[PDB]
C-alpha cells in the first residue's frame, strides 16, 4: 500500500524507486551504506522515513 | 479513468468564472469628453455674421487653437454651418483647468509625461507599508504613509 | 541496460550496448575486444554512446568527473545535459543534476561537472548517459577505476 | 487589426504627388516636378505637416474598434506574465518545533542574475525536514523560464536551512500577449453564452483550466470512446493540463464542477484525460553557411517547439509533413533535402479524435558548401531512461 500518495516522515512523497530507507533511530538525511552479504554489494541509502 | 457530471444549479467553481463582461468607462476615444462645465463659467453668446470659432477663441480665450475648447463646450461639428442668432457657449479663461503638461524632470528615462501624478512613480502610497489593518484605514482617510514614531517606551 | 541487470565493469571491453533511444539513433557494430556489440550514434561511428551508473563507496549520488578536457558549450535542457567541445569532437552527458559548470567555462579531464542525482529527490534515481569517442570513454573508465586522472 | 487605409501619408509620396498635382492644376505653367529639386523645401514643409496629420486621421476606425473592445467589453491589458515555479526547501536537521521559510524569500541560480521570490510563508511541520512552495520571477519576460534543478542558491543564510531547489521548470513567463490571441479572446467573450458547440466547450474548459491548457470536445461519445456507437445527450471532454500533460483527476473534477451549472439539463458530461503521440523527426538539410551548425540546430529546435506547442496544435488532426517542412525552413539559411517522421516520409494520422502530437526527438544531418556534414541527435522529452 505504500505508493506515491503516502508521505514519508521526512515530508516528501514516497518514491518507491528511490534509493532510500526508513531507520528506527537515525536522523533524516543520514547516509547509510547497506552491504548485502550474498553478493558483497553495497549501496548508500538516504534515511528519510521512519 | 473518466467521470460523469450531471447538471447542477449552483456551484462555486462556475461562480468564479461567471463575471466576464465588465463595462468600465476608462480612457478611450469616446470617454475623452466626460467632464462638462456648467453655466457658472460659460458665456451665452449669439452667432452673428462674420463670426467663427477662430475669432471667438482669439477674443475670449486669446489662443487661436483654443477653439476646440469652445467646440467641446457646445458639442457641435465645426465644419457644419451654425445659423445666425444661435446661442453658443464660450468658456471663460478665468475659471478653467490649466492645460499645462506635467513632467518629472529627474527620471530614470530623463523626462516623462504624467497625467495625474498618482499613477506614476511619485506615488509613495505603498512605501514602508505595514499590512496591519490600522494603517490601511488611516491611508484611506488621510493618506498617512510613514509612522512618526516606533518607540519601545 | 534496460532489460539486463546492472553489472560492475572495469573497462569498456566488458559491457553491453544500450537501447535504441527515442527514435533509434543507435547503430551496433562489432569491434575487436568488446564482449558485446558496440553502440554508436547515427552517422557517427566514432562517437559511441553508453548508459552506466557511477558509484563511490556505494553511493550513486557521487559527483561526476569530466571525461574529457575542453570548453563547455551547453548546460541544462529537458534532461540534465552537459556538452563539451574538445576541439575535434563533442562529448555529451545526460541525466546530470546540480550542474556546477557554466557555458563557456574551461574544464579539464576529471573536473566535477555535477551530480548524478540531486539531493532534493528530483526523481531521486537515474543513470549517466555519455556520448564520446572510444579513446575518451576507455580512458574515462580507466581513470574512474584507478583514480589517476 | 486590418483597418482599411483612408488616405496616403507616405512622406515622399506626398511630395511627389503634390508636385505632379501642382503641375496638373496650373495647366503646365508649373514644370518643377523634381522630387529633389528647388521646390523640395516647400513641398517637404507641407508634407511634414500633412503626413503627421493624416497618420492620426487614419487611426479613426481602429480607435473606435479598440474603444468598443475596451469599454463595453472591459478586456484586461496583458502587461506580461512572470514565470512561476515550485521550490523545495530542505532543512539541516529534524527540528522539535515548526519551521517557517518567510514569504518573499529570494532564491537564484549559480550566476545570481535570475532571481525568484517565494509566494507565501512555507511551514515545515515539526519532525519533517522538508517543505515545498511556489515562487514567482523577479520580473516579467521569457528569460525567466528555466529548467528543473536550475535554481539552487538562496542569498539570506537562514538558520537550520540547508538547501533549496526547483522541482518544476519555470514556465508561463511572457513579456506581453500577441494581438491575434487578444482578438480571439475578445471574440470568444462575445460568443460563449450557453456552451453548445465543440468550440464553446473547448474554449470554456481551457479558459477555466488556465493559460497553457488544451481541450477537445466530442459529441455523443460514451465512456467506451467508440465513435460507431453514438449516444445523444452526451458530451465527452478531453483535457491537457497547464503543464502539457494529460489532466490530473483533480483538474478533471475542477473543470467538471465549473461546467456543471452550465450544461443543458438532462444531458450527460464526460471528462477524461487526453492522449499524446510521440513524434520522431530526422532532418537532412543543406546549409548556406550563413549560420553556424549549432545556431541552425537551436533555431530549428525553437521553431519545432513553437510548431508542436499544444496551443498551436489541434487535437485529432493529422501532422502534415509539408507543414513541418515549412516550419523548419522558415528558420532560414538552409535548404531541406529530406525529412522523416516516425521512420517515414508520409503524413501521420492520430490514433483517435483526442490525441495531440508532442515531438520528442530530432536528428540533424546538416551539410554545407565546404562539405562538412554536421550530424546530431537531440531528445526533447524529459526521458530519464535515455
Image (cartoon, coloured by chain):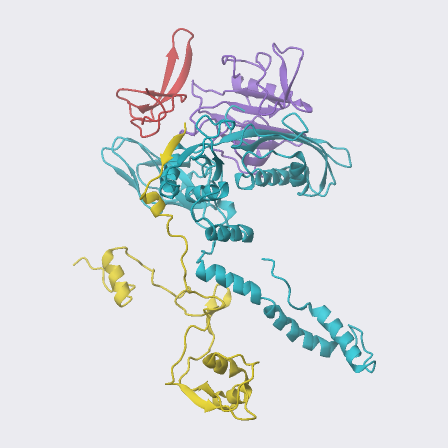
Q: Can residue D176 be seen in this view?
A: no
| Pick the front one: D207 or D116 | D207
Which chain is rendered purple in the image?
C
Is residue C11 visible in the rendered image? The answer is yes
Residue B130 in the image: above or below residue B77: above
- Chain painted yellow: B
Q: Of residues B27 and C87, which is closer to you in this image?
A: B27
User: Relative to C58, is D160 above or below?
Assistant: below
Residue at 52% x, 12% y is: C4
Residue B137 location, x and y as percent? 25, 62
Tint of chain A: red
Q: In the rendered view, does D37 fall on the left or right side of C124?
A: right
Q: Position of residue D48 (x, y in %)?
A: 66, 73
Colour cyan, chain: D
Which quadrant of the figure has residue D313?
A: top right
Q: In this view, does B118 lie above or below B80?
A: above
Give x and y (percent) for residue D324. 64, 37
Amino acid at each position: 500500500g505504500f505508493d506515491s500518495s503516502d508521505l514519508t516522515a521526512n515530508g516528501e512523497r514516497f518514491n518507491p524507486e528511490g534509493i532510500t530507507a526508513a531507520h528506527e533511530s537515525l536522523p533524516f538525511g543520514t547516509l547509510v551504506k547497506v552491504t548485502w552479504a550474498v553478493n558483497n554489494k553495497s549501496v548508500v541509502v538516504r534515511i528519510n522515513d521512519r | 479513468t473518466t467521470q460523469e457530471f450531471l447538471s447542477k444549479n449552483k456551484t462555486i467553481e462556475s461562480e468564479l468564472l461567471d463575471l466576464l463582461i465588465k463595462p468600465n468607462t476608462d480612457d478611450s476615444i469616446l470617454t475623452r469628453n466626460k467632464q462638462a462645465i456648467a453655466d457658472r463659467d460659460l458665456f451665452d453668446i449669439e452667432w452673428e455674421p462674420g463670426q467663427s470659432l477662430n475669432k471667438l477663441a482669439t477674443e475670449y480665450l486669446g489662443d487661436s487653437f483654443a477653439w476646440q475648447i469652445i467646440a467641446d463646450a457646445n458639442g457641435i461639428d465645426p465644419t457644419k454651418e451654425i445659423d445666425i442668432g444661435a446661442g453658443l457657449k464660450v468658456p471663460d479663461q478665468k475659471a478653467l483647468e490649466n492645460s499645462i503638461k506635467k513632467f518629472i524632470v529627474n527620471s530614470p528615462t530623463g523626462k516623462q509625461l504624467i497625467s495625474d501624478a498618482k499613477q506614476s512613480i511619485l506615488n509613495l502610497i505603498g512605501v514602508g507599508d505595514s499590512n496591519t489593518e490600522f494603517s490601511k484605514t488611516l491611508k484611506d482617510c488621510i493618506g498617512k504613509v510613514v509612522n512618526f514614531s516606533f518607540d519601545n517606551t | 541496460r534496460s532489460g539486463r541487470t546492472v553489472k560492475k565493469i572495469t573497462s569498456l571491453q566488458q559491457s553491453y550496448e544500450h537501447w535504441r533511444g527515442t527514435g533509434g539513433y543507435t547503430a551496433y557494430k562489432q569491434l575487436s575486444g568488446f564482449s558485446s556489440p558496440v553502440s554508436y550514434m547515427k552517422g557517427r561511428p566514432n562517437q559511441l554512446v553508453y548508459d552506466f551508473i557511477l558509484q563511490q563507496n556505494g553511493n550513486q549520488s557521487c559527483p561526476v568527473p569530466s571525461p574529457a578536457s575542453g570548453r563547455v558549450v551547453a548546460t541544462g535542457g529537458s534532461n540534465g545535459m552537459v556538452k563539451i567541445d574538445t576541439g575535434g569532437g563533442e562529448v555529451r552527458l545526460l541525466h546530470m543534476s546540480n550542474i556546477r559548470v557554466k557555458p563557456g567555462q574551461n574544464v579539464i579531464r576529471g573536473t566535477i561537472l555535477g551530480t548524478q542525482a540531486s539531493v532534493g529527490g528530483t526523481s531521486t534515481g537515474t543513470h549517466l548517459h555519455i556520448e564520446a569517442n572510444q579513446f575518451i570513454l576507455e580512458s574515462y573508465v580507466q581513470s574512474l577505476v584507478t583514480g589517476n586522472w | 487589426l486590418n483597418a482599411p487605409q483612408l488616405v496616403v501619408d507616405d512622406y515622399e509620396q506626398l511630395i511627389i504627388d503634390s508636385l505632379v498635382h501642382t503641375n496638373v492644376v496650373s495647366n503646365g505653367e508649373f514644370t518643377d516636378l523634381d522630387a529633389s529639386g528647388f521646390m523640395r523645401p516647400f513641398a517637404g514643409t507641407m508634407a511634414y505637416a500633412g503626413s503627421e496629420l493624416l497618420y492620426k486621421a487614419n487611426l479613426a476606425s481602429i480607435a473606435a474598434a479598440k474603444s468598443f473592445f475596451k469599454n463595453v467589453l472591459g478586456v484586461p491589458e496583458d502587461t506580461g506574465t512572470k514565470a512561476t515555479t515550485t521550490l523545495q526547501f530542505g532543512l539541516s536537521a529534524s527540528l522539535s518545533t515548526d519551521f517557517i521559510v518567510p514569504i518573499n524569500f529570494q532564491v537564484s541560480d549559480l550566476s545570481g542574475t535570475l532571481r525568484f521570490y517565494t509566494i507565501g510563508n512555507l511551514v515545515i511541520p515539526a519532525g519533517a525536514t522538508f517543505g515545498t512552495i511556489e515562487a514567482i520571477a523577479e520580473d516579467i519576460g521569457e528569460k525567466y523560464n528555466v529548467s528543473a534543478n536550475f535554481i539552487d542558491q538562496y542569498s539570506t543564510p537562514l538558520t537550520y536551512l540547508q538547501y533549496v531547489t526547483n522541482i518544476r521548470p519555470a514556465t508561463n513567463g511572457r513579456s506581453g500577449e500577441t494581438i491575434d490571441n487578444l482578438i480571439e479572446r475578445c471574440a470568444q467573450i462575445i460568443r460563449i453564452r450557453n456552451p453548445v458547440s465543440a468550440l464553446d466547450f473547448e474554449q470554456l474548459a481551457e479558459l477555466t483550466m488556465g493559460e497553457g491548457s488544451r481541450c477537445k470536445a466530442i459529441g455523443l461519445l460514451g465512456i467506451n470512446k467508440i465513435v460507431t456507437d453514438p449516444q445523444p445527450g452526451v458530451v465527452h471532454l478531453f483535457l491537457l493540463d497547464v503543464n502539457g500533460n494529460p489532466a490530473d483527476p483533480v483538474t478533471i473534477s475542477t473543470v467538471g464542477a465549473t461546467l456543471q451549472p452550465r450544461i443543458m439539463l438532462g444531458t450527460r458530461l464526460l471528462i477524461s484525460p487526453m492522449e499524446v503521440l510521440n513524434i520522431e523527426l530526422e532532418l537532412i538539410a543543406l546549409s548556406d553557411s550563413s549560420k553556424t551548425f549549432q545556431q541552425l540546430a537551436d533555431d530549428i529546435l525553437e521553431a519545432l517547439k513553437v510548431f508542436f506547442n499544444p496551443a498551436n496544435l489541434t487535437p485529432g488532426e493529422p501532422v502534415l509533413i509539408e507543414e513541418v517542412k515549412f516550419a523548419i525552413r522558415s528558420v532560414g539559411g538552409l535548404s531541406i533535402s529530406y525529412l522523416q517522421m516516425n521512420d517515414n516520409a508520409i503524413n501521420i494520422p492520430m490514433p483517435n479524435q483526442w490525441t495531440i502530437p508532442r515531438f520528442s526527438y530530432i536528428g540533424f544531418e546538416l551539410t554545407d558548401s565546404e562539405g562538412t556534414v554536421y550530424r546530431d541527435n537531440v531528445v526533447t522529452v524529459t526521458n530519464p531512461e535515455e
